[PDB]
Image (cartoon, rainbow, N blue to C red; front, side, top):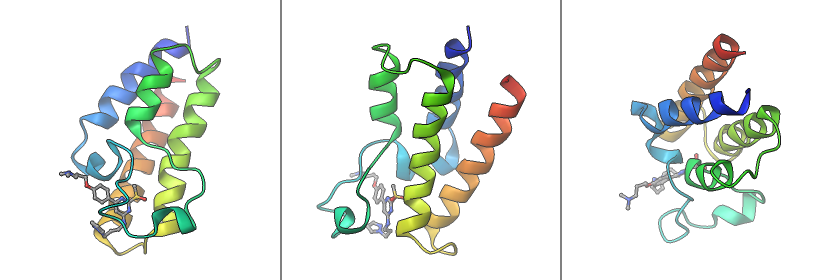
Length: 102
Ligand SMILES: CN(C)CCCOc1ccc(-c2cc(NCCCn3cccn3)nc(S(C)(=O)=O)n2)cc1
């Protein structure tokens, strides 16, 4: 019953104005040397793939992947960059919705 809310939250994040950096895996042709720094990439497409296939055994596991998206953003980008700002917006949005649903 808790896992059904993850799809709803995922859809809301996919639709958010600030979500553009996170929709698909980082493209290494666009973001030079990404994997030198980010050893465990994550993105909303990968999360959708796993959620749709029972790859999350609990809502907590889904939340951990959401936070990994934002933690990787914060590790790679300065807070005042456009992508860094987007990550902070999305983390706040995610955490707020998580509290409402749970
Ligand atoms: C072809 N299709 C329309 C592309 C649409 C999506 O394009 C993206 C998506 C995500 C990025 C990107 C970048 C970045 N740090 C660098 C910021 C400076 N920058 C370098 C290249 C571009 N901007 N960090 C991150 S993340 C996920 O670690 O926070 N994600 C980039 C492009």
